[PDB]
Every structure is written in C-alpha cells, then in structure tokens.
Amino acid sequence: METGDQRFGDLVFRQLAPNVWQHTSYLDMGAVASNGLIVRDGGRVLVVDTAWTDDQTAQILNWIKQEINLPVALAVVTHAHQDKMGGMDALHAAGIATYANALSNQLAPQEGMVAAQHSLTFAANGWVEPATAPNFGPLKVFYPGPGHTSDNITVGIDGTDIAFGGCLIKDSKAKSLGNLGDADTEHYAASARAFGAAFPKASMIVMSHSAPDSRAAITHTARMADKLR
Ligand SMILES: O=C(O)[C@@H]1CS[C@H]2CS[C@H](CS)N21
Ligand SMILES: [Zn+2]
Ligand SMILES: [Zn+2]
C-alpha cells in the first residue's frame, strides 16, 4: 500500500488518472491482491471486474458512492475466476448491468460463480461486437486469444494511456506465468502480443496481480510464454 492510496474497509484504491482508479481486494490463501478498475465517464461510473467476494464488492460500491458520488451504470468482468467474478451478486443487488465474454458466462456455473446478465461476443479480429457492448463509453473491449484462460478479455480506456491486461499480463519482474491447467500454452505468447498490438499507445499497463507497469510487462510476459511452446 503506497502513499496516495486510499483504504475503505478491506479495499485499497489508487487514482491512476483524473477519471480512473484501481481497486484492490485481498483474499487470504497470505493476503493475495487482485486489481480491477473504476472509470468516471461524464455523469456515470463504469467498473471493470468485481472483488473476490460479494461483501468486498459492496465495499467498492460504497466507496464509489462516498468518494465519487455518481451512479454505476455497468460492470464488465474479464474472466470466470473468483477474483474477477466473485462479487457478481453484489452488483446485481445494486441494480448494475453486468457484462462478460459469453464463454465466461458459460463457464461461471461450473466454477460456482454467478454469470453476468449479458454476454459479449467478438469478431474474428478480436474486437468486441459493438451491439453486445452498448453504451460502453470509453471502454474498448478486446479478446486477444487464449492465454491465461480460454475466456480472458482485456480493456483499454479511451482518452487515457491506460490498458487493462487482467490476469493475462504479468509484471515485468515476474518469475513465472503461474500458468495452470486452463492456460493455452501454445497461443499464450501470441495472445499477449495481440493485446499489445490492440492498444499500441497504452503506456500504463494495469493487471490483476501486480501494480501498474510499463509496456515491458507485455514483452516480458510474451517472453515467458515463448518458453512454454
Ligand atoms: O494465478 C494467480 O496468480 C492468481 C493468484 S492465486 C490464483 C487463484 S485465484 C487467481 C486466479 S487468476 N489466482
Ligand atoms: Zn484468472
Ligand atoms: Zn487473477
């Protein structure tokens, strides 16, 4: 927890830009961090990823109400793991519209997760079909291909130098990819590089389990992935 960070309950918030904050929640497994984003877009707020749990995700919503005081219009979640979708019910209880890759929603029940209300689909070039992501404002959603998981998606924030790699991208000092059973080790490297190419001017790379990094996180991640093919 660095200087300039705010704490609300068990959550930590770091402002990254005038209209963007990183939310961080922890699960004791020894407190393992997971990062998401909060975006102020005019008179509304957009959320990328829940916290680990419903209660933690409610803390995010209370912090937003208290510190930003704008309604949360929608949330997009970036794949079907507990750190990204664990608080879906808290969002739904607040009347927030939720979006995920169709595959994430298909996987959610098997994972003991609650599926989002709406499914995103993607063109062959990886960009989201705009009709499935209505009124996403500055959020530009890109499916880079299979990597960390088959369903992982990524998000750039228009008007900023920020892109969110989710759990696909590791920080540039990482000693391993942590890749498990559901990783695609054949395509991981190409998918990391695809994320980089989709958001070629993003200079701040936000990710799920490390603090924000430079684009070196992308190239370092791709190098680690090259070794697995
Ligand atoms: O693989 C990881 O590094 C992170 C932290 S521990 C492991 C279990 S939950 C979450 C899924 S991305 N995760
Ligand atoms: Zn994951
Ligand atoms: Zn994760």
Image (cartoon, grey):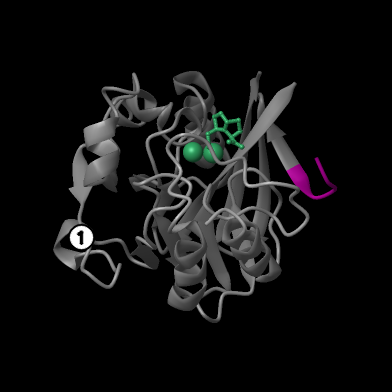
Q: Residue at x 64, y 64 (%)?
A: 223
Tell me where residue 76 appears, x and y as whole percent: 36, 47
Label 1 beta carbon less than 8 Å to ligand 2: no
Closer to us: 124 or 21: 124
Closer to us: 227 or 44: 227
Tell me where residue 172 appears, x and y as whole percent: 73, 60
- Image vertical order of residue 197 relative to residue 79, above or below: below
Q: Quadrant of the N terminus?
A: top right
The overriding secondary structure of the stretch rendered in magenta is loop
Q: Is residue 97 visible?
A: no
Tell me where residue 151 appears, x and y as whole percent: 34, 46
Give the farthest residue toward the left. 131
Give the farthest residue toward the bottom. 201
Name which residue type carries label 1: Pro
Q: Residue at x 47, y 26 (%)?
A: 58
> Which residue is the site of mark 1?
134
* SS assignment at label 1: loop
